[PDB]
Image (cartoon, rainbow over the protein chains, first blue to last red):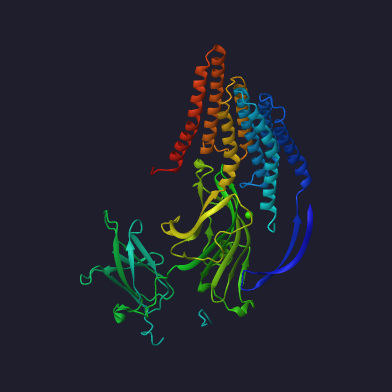
Length: 158
Length: 444
Ligand SMILES: [Ca+2]
């Protein structure tokens, strides 16, 4: 979608010692951000929501099963939307966010494994403390990463 | 400026045309051949230092008489033929020998070296009909594509040749305009249009026809012509070796050969009219570590050689992308498959092992989009195979541990568990060290 356009005439050093006249039409275009927000980011936020709410039932075996299943779901969804992800040779803020989300889901799988070990060894108070600590840090980790990426890739003044 | 050309017999002694040079003989150029410019009717050629003098058509004209003082052979000739061209050729290999090096100097004069008697000879004019000196400049604006299965790279850039040909000069008034310009026609096409020699070039590796844009060859009345062309050309790259992908460094070699031998034109000087590699907005897939432009000689299709101007760009992939997207999630999946050996419930461990192997397969194909479908293996493919083998192995070990837990042996199961804990990281580290030694070092 064309945000703005502008036609204007300049001079350019021609092949000889003189200059040629140039007429440049610049169109400021942008993507349909609604499509990416509703197709890529909303299902993703739901997958993180599942991986964050599995820390409520604290059965520690059911939690582990759902954590592994949700990591598999995240992989499958990532490749489902990989069709529109451009196969550019360099990183992108969408790629960076997918990367961070996958690392955090794998980390919650690891924490579920450790919590299951704690539940089996006989330490459940420590397991509950780790559980509530995950509940409090996970949303702030995601918010901090989003703020950091916004500051890095969209601002210079602030 | 003082004008020379053609329009519509005294004091010839001062205008003596006599000059000398030193030569080096080695490798294939044992036989040396030199031409000369058109001569006056009275001019007599004296050759001093076998050797033989013929015309442009090769018809023998004179040999050399060996005079022992001064060594070598002395040759002399004279003719009254008006418009004609003469050639002197010297052969240094009359028999098979090891050789390997030869230093040689010659004495050449078109009228009378006796008057000059060699010496410094400042007023001497070169009469070898020396090859025209063409400067070349090349700039790269983008590397638009790299097809690594077909091993080619499409590159866009600008090319600028510049050569002085007095025969190409003209009177500015006859056409009005000062500069005579031939648009959107190759140097070969212009040489076809006007029956004159021009330094036609080629890229020596392009597949298909390059897109030539803004190409124009314009001549100045003094005779200094210049050719400009913004090309979009798909070069072939045999030198590509993706065995170390994605940690590989590649050479993008853009080689502009001249379609005329070294006798006619040679690339004199590389011209830095524009930044050799352009800086453009964006990270870009291939970042240029270093570039280097240089001129060489290549055996031409005839017995002579042509001048080649090669621009070599040392490019590398954005390794942050591969490390953060391919290797970090891979390390996390491996960490899951290694930490499933802590809970030791032996049924939950098996469930998570199977689920994690499925996760590994799904992630493998998720990142298979960027894995090149090359017909041969790669360090990334090798590491993926090792990871899959180890994950399947931990699935098998989990099955065996579950069997041991069910049979009534749990101490052996715990021993196997801790043994897996201690060997798995060292297995991965050992494999990484081995692949680094195999694919990145020779000294160590
Ligand atoms: Ca760019």
